[PDB]
Image: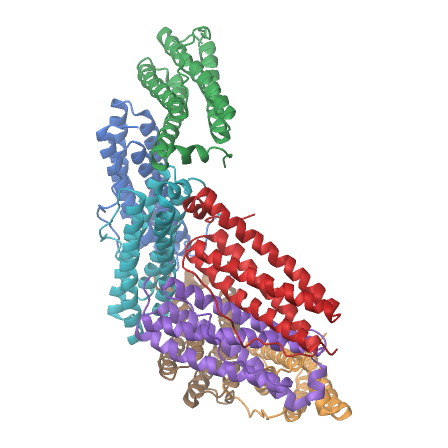
Chain colours: A blue, B cyan, C green, D red, E purple, F brown, G orange
Amino acid sequence: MKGDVKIINYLNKLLGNELVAINQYFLHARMFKNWGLMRLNDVEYHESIDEHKHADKYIERILFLEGIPNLQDLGKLGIGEDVEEMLQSDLALELEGADDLREAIAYADSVHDYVSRDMMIEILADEEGHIDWLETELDLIGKIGLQNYLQSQIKVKD
Amino acid sequence: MKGDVKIINYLNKLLGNELVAINQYFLHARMFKNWGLMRLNDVEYHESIDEHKHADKYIERILFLEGIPNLQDLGKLGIGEDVEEMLQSDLALELEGADDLREAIAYADSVHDYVSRDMMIEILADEEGHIDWLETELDLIGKIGLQNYLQSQIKVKD
Amino acid sequence: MKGDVKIINYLNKLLGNELVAINQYFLHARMFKNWGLMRLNDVEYHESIDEHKHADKYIERILFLEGIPNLQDLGKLGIGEDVEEMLQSDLALELEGADDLREAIAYADSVHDYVSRDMMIEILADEEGHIDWLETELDLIGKIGLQNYLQSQIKVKD
Amino acid sequence: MKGDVKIINYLNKLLGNELVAINQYFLHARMFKNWGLMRLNDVEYHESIDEHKHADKYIERILFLEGIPNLQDLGKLGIGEDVEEMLQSDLALELEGADDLREAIAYADSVHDYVSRDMMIEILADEEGHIDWLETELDLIGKIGLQNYLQSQIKVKD
Amino acid sequence: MKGDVKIINYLNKLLGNELVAINQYFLHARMFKNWGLMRLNDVEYHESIDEHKHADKYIERILFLEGIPNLQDLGKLGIGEDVEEMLQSDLALELEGADDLREAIAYADSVHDYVSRDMMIEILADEEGHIDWLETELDLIGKIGLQNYLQSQIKVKD
Amino acid sequence: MKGDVKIINYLNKLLGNELVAINQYFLHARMFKNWGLMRLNDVEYHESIDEHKHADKYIERILFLEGIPNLQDLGKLGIGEDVEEMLQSDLALELEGADDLREAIAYADSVHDYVSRDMMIEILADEEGHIDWLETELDLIGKIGLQNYLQSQIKVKD
Amino acid sequence: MKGDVKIINYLNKLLGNELVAINQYFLHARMFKNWGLMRLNDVEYHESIDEHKHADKYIERILFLEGIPNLQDLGKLGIGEDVEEMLQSDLALELEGADDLREAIAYADSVHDYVSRDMMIEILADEEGHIDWLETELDLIGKIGLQNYLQSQIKVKD
């Protein structure tokens, strides 16, 4: 089904956001694992998987609309050297991406691509869930102190 | 544990090959899926997952050796426009990657990093499996013709 | 709960669309069955049941909003005589209905009937799923040939 | 228990036919597998195992008759280069073996070795089973054409 | 995948060794069975199957490397004439086979065929396991005497 | 099977390394247990059992190669008086043993004892896992402080 | 809880006895295994594990009493070359250890360390069980002959 040209541009821009986040969450997780912080490895690894599902949704939607998914252009990763800096970098990316989503969701409504809009609103709800988790972990670091914070990321999560 | 510097560079080279293969296999699968070729979607997607496991092994090895994994630089994808071109692109990529593995395996032996070598030999055996499958599929297109070959990619695989 | 008058007219229009698609998919299914193409019988019969579920939603929403559902006026069916015309007739009908849906969804937003809008977006997502299946089948006929295509519709689908 | 001298010669000849068939069927199976024809791999491999069961009966019978089984002299294999050539080679080998069995069965009756005869008649019934299968596969190639025939050897039989 | 020409020659030599050992172990097992030594029949028959697995590995690797497996030339069998002679012949054949493996494995590393090397090293480990069993049985004959040794081969093994 | 003289000397040296580790990890474990650090008792004891498994492989390999295992000469233990010192002593011993393994793996290749080499490469990957665990614990002491670190060694690990 | 100084010396002496018996029984077990005498491997390996449990008791009791367990000094092993010498070496070692135990038990009673005494009496009962097994086996060699004795150690024990 032939889709709106600018829609496919937005969808590719959003896909680009997800591709960065996949790699960044993935490296961050294995850095936590290498440091022995297995609880952070598990949550960050799962958020890597979650952005991969978002990428999948964007890719399949673009192909349906008869556009060309762009997996070639990788934006800038922000890795960071300790726990606080990694979580902060993930949080910066997530907000940047939420800002892009809000713009695409508004445009999708103006051209009546309501199914693309609905897909994006659901993805936006997922990313605001990641944002909530990231802000909460960062606040905990301040409240309980870095040594206590790291201590309780050693063993794994239910 | 401090690793050999040139070992870390090879590991990052081989990591970069897998990062390209993850994305190429991922897009190829969903193109197959969009065309209704569910058997090809299943196999190509599973090889994307399998290249992700290879990348995970490089990443974790690089960190253990106290190097820095490079997930930022993404090499050139070769997407291709129809089934035969896509399969041939994947094959070209797999042959380039086996070439790098053989050089890396030879070097790792010279500096006595026998665990990095054992890891890479296992990965090379996997990749020769992928090569075997691609060569076999490409030969079958010729043996039974494109229409028959595509027909039997419609329904899924056991 | 009294609803917007123009909303009830849009709902009845959309209901009219589903009523023709129920009948068209039903007859097409049994034509496929009569020809021994049981995989097409199964899929088309199932889409007939789906359009019946959509019609149910319209009927119940119209009665809730204290309007009168119109099941009397039946639009123009396009039956066709062979597989490729039957699928293309079904594709034309779905694109026309997606057109009407996009107009009703935009109007529902302007008079603040957000529940009717939400129900129509979910129906529009279903119809875009039907459109994808129809386009994909029609393309496979061109990719594998009509004789191969008909052959792989003989036996039934998982 | 002392066997008739010429009976042991006949058993060793028949044993030699089975040894050629084991190797020929074995290589043919793995050529089919290499080509992706998993159905042909499965059938030809089982027939290789069937001929091993026949060799086992000859070897055990020869030893019981206090002869010396000959597993040293291997006759001429006829491998063949494509599917039709390979099946025609197996058919020729099977018809040659049936010819030897009939002569041995007639002779066993004349010296009252009725147990060796009964064993050979069962084996001959097996080999006429293999001949039936090969003749049917060769005829199918003619009826449905080589491309369709190879296509339906891709996925596995039940 | 085009393999190294001298690799394929080594693979066919090693395959030749396995084909001799398949037959020798097979016949030896059934001679033990004929003598009522059921425990030796069981082990020797199992070792015949194991050498068949190794032959299968060589055949499939050669075809992958686009060579021609040689199942035609069968080297000399050394049957032997009582229990200890048969075991010594198996041992002599295994030591000859392990000698050839050592040379192929070294050559494979020089031409960077690391997967063929890995396969042969795993086969060599199996062969050193057979050698250990053979050496152990030979030593037992000398410690407990042939009458006691044969007695404990009558009933079967867990 | 007559083994290379030096190979047996390398294997007895590596066996010597394992025998000191068995005793050091054994004593360290029960010292942790006496201090109520049950998580560290659990892990260290397990590593003592793991080195005993390594010792077992060296002993069986040396006897198979017709050497004589030396279990008499016990090298210098480095017990240590507090947790950080004990872990650093284990780390030092593991790095010394890995150094010896690398020399022996190089030598074993030069004389074509590929099965001994394969065994020692597997052991070496196990010891690099032990090294990884030791380095991570020692870094965690730095990052969360000794008091917190000891605290989360009190209760046992999943 | 601070213990009697001479009690800790007795405990370390007794611990030294168990440390040599662990190694001697271990090597003897695998020598039996290398020779194919699996029933003797099983029994001797199990006694090695038993002496390891005794050593554990000594180590934990010494640490409880605030002494320093000595795992560094390893007494003189007597390995031997054949079954009857290996068993007789094991018997001499056990009788020497029973001697030391009897002395330590009498001393523990005089300084009122009744818990250390009770633990040593239970260990002494175990060692008298080992002595009984060794004397009984050695006597069977004389009653049934060495060739019969070795024969009935080939297969494993219930």
The spot of residue G142 in percent (x, y) is 75, 93
Q: Nearer the viewer, residue G100 or G76?
A: G76
F106 to the left or right of C26 = left
The image position of residue E52, as x and y in percent, is 52, 69
Choose top left, top right, bottom left or bottom right for residue D47: bottom right
- What x and y, as percent, mark residue G44? 64, 82
Left/right of residue F154 with respect to residue G135 in the rendered view: left
Quadrant occupied by the N terminus of chain E: bottom left
Decide if residue D3 is in sight here.
Answer: yes
Q: Nearer the viewer, residue F17 or F154?
A: F17
Instruction: Give the total number of marks visible in the rendering.
Output: 0
Q: Is residue E158 visible?
A: no
Residue drawn at x 66%, y 82% as measured from the top left: G40
Quarter holding the C terminus of chain E?
Answer: bottom right
The answer to whether residue G103 is above or below residue F92 is below
Residue sitting at x 65%, y 57%: D125
Q: What percent of the width, then of the height, locates residue E11?
A: 40, 72
Left or right position of D112 against C90: right
Q: Residue at x 52, y 57 (%)?
A: D91
Depicted B100 relative to depicted F31: above or below: above
In terms of depth relative to the viewer, which is nearer, D76 or G116?
D76
In the displayed image of the protein, which residue is found farthest to the right?
G143
Residue E111, quarter of picture:
bottom left
